[PDB]
Image: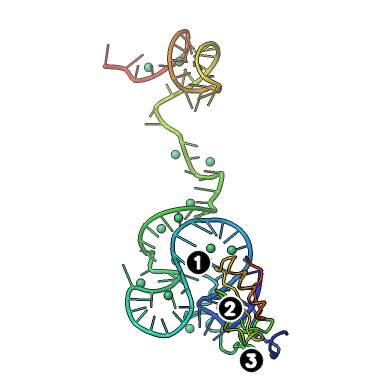
RNA sequence: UGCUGUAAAGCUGGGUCGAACGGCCUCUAGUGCAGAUCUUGGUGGUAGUAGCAAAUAUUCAAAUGAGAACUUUGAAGACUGA
């Protein structure tokens, strides 16, 4: 890791917690919703049903919010936004906003390279 | 295209697009949908399916026309049967 050293990153659950029967019906979106029904096999945690979000899956407080490269990602919309990452170049990486123009994005990439700030999305437009 | 969060979700690559829009500190509410034989609109399977079967009955040729079972004319065969 080129960032500040961290313990090995553990993700207790790496899949997406998908709402029950978001596979059965198009009207039911995958966005997680807690079953509230009286008879629900999922709400009652029958064997073979889907896993559900709970605080036990919470991330280690030392590796939380770190991308696979070991950085915390900060959203940048202009070159002045990189000033808050001057003393945090080994723990914070910059991510250029999608709505920044192709002109201003070149300036942000140019200044980040000068400051040593890492950019998580360095190519797009 | 991926990243972050236990999660609600947030951010991002590519495509499309054409005029507005967001972060944060607060304020406010007509603020979150899978159901209500919910409302309005739209779309399926059914399915090229049920079916298009009462009232006797049509046929040959020519003309017209891009095209004629169905139009026009002629010839015939019928019917309504005052
Ligand atoms: Mg019960
Ligand atoms: Mg784009
Ligand atoms: Mg756009
Ligand atoms: Mg316009
Ligand atoms: Mg504002
Ligand atoms: Mg309401
Ligand atoms: Mg609905
Ligand atoms: Mg309806
Ligand atoms: Mg239908
Ligand atoms: Mg039929
Ligand atoms: Mg019938
Ligand atoms: Mg005739
Ligand atoms: Mg007679």
How far apart, in angstroms, are the residues tagged by discs 2 and 1? 17 Å
How far apart, in angstroms, are the residues tagged by discs 1 and 3? 39 Å
How far apart, in angstroms, are the residues tagged by discs 2 and 3? 23 Å
Q: Which mark is residue A17?
A: 2
| Residue on which disc 3 sits | A62
Which secondary structure, mark 2?
loop
Host chain of mark 2: A
Q: Give the percent coordinates (x, y) of residue A5.
A: 70, 90
Q: Within 10 angstroms of label 3, few (less than 14), some, or many (20 or more) residues?
A: few
Q: Give the percent coordinates (x, y) of residue B10.
A: 53, 76
Q: Give the percent coordinates (x, y) of residue A101.
A: 56, 66
Eyeballing the image, is A54 above or below B50?
Answer: below
Q: Quadrant of the N terminus of chain A?
A: bottom right
Q: Within 10 angstroms of label 1, few (less than 14), some, or many (20 or more) residues?
A: few
Give the residue at x 62% y 69%.
Answer: A106
2 or 3: mark nearer the eye: 3
Give the residue at x 60% y 81%.
Answer: A51
Nearest to the observer: residue A107 or residue A52: A107
Q: Are marks 2 and 1 in contact (CB under 8 Å)?
A: no
Which secondary structure, mark 1?
loop
Q: Which mark is residue A27?
A: 1
1 or 3: mark nearer the eye: 3
């Amino acid at each position: 890791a080129t960032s500040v050293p961290h313990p090995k990153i553990v993700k207790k659950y790496t899949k997406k917690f998908k709402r029950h029967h978001s596979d059965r019906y198009h009207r039911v979106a995958e966005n997680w919703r807690k079953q509230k029904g009286i008879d629900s096999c999922v709400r009652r945690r029958f064997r073979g049903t889907i896993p559900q979000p709970n605080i036990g899956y919470g991330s280690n407080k030392k590796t939380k919010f770190l991308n696979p490269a070991g950085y915390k990602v900060y959203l940048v919309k202009n070159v002045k936004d990189l000033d808050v990452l001057l003393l945090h170049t080994k723990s914070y990486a910059a991510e250029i906003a999608s709505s920044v123009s192709s002109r201003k994005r070149v300036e942000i990439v140019a200044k980040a390279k000068k400051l040593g700030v890492k950019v998580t999305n360095p190519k797009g437009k």
